[PDB]
Length: 281
Ligand SMILES: CCCCCCOc1cccc(Cn2ccc(O)c(C(=O)O)c2=O)c1
Ligand SMILES: [Mg+2]
Ligand SMILES: [Mg+2]
Ligand SMILES: [Mg+2]
Image 1 (tube, helix red, strand yellow):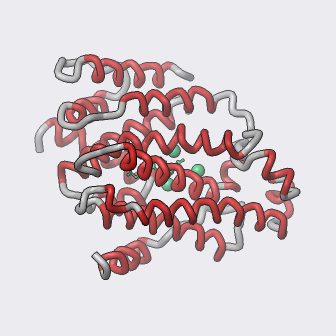
Image 2 (tube, protein in one colour):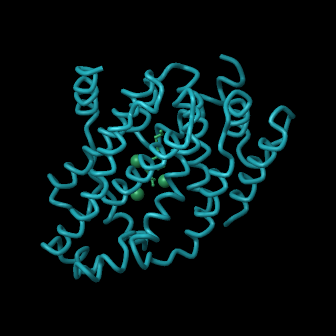
């Protein structure tokens, strides 16, 4: 394998370490598109994890800026060379939405002084910032002729996936001093996350959970309805990634909404879902 191959392999490793679901699905893509997703995904992970000060994140942002300004120049990257070298390689062949990386970065800067979200509007704006932006960056990789609707579908999918993630992680997020449900919705449903964490679920909580799960599932259906904005090769894969991810909701239900472990979709169940999906492709 070439030096660049090694860079992409490292990007793969970061993706698979962070998400078996997304790696499971996206490693099914043809080589070229597969590798581009690894790099973009790895950059987004490095960004999301960075603060845990801002130094490295400033360096990531500066590296991304160098690539945007001078895609074909050799740069001595300040942050992670392997990842930036791969991103640069991708950017030389695809139209990367750099402002989307900057939106993600800005959101991550903001998460430092995390304050709970007043309304759902603020929560959904967060979902765009950390996840819709990722859909936007992935768009040119996963579609042939991108237009406003391609970006919109990808953005909505990203956002739904984030919401599902939040719904899986209420417990662990609370332990790390984060509550992503909005005050508006929490107060409406009469839920105190600390209280549920100490005492177990009740009917108020389950109702609030199901309110957000309803939103996620409906967005999923609307994304599926528009699957054809994506390249034919990427369609079943994107569908798969979504389906695997939405199955998480049922795992949460089957575990009775527990706030004390991370539920998951077995590897063998992921294979079943994929089989299901191709019985129509
Ligand atoms: C057309 C392209 C389809 C769009 C794909 C978007 O992929 C993304 C991007 C960003 C976030 C998520 C949700 N997600 C999943 C696992 C996870 O661990 C976290 C976390 O750690 O928060 C998390 O947010 C998914
Ligand atoms: Mg995940
Ligand atoms: Mg994220
Ligand atoms: Mg989470």
